[PDB]
Length: 40
Image (cartoon, rainbow, N blue to C red; front, side):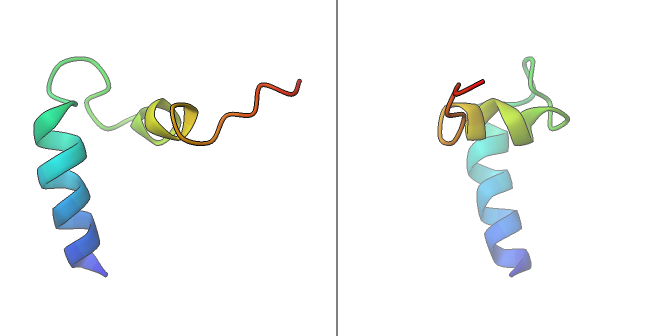
């Protein structure tokens, strides 16, 4: 689904990435705001 990539990129990238997350660690950045349970 490269379209999902181009989309997430156009979105998650253009709207927040060329600042700090860039794209590395982004994987955790949003997942953190969308996944991290903080159990341990």
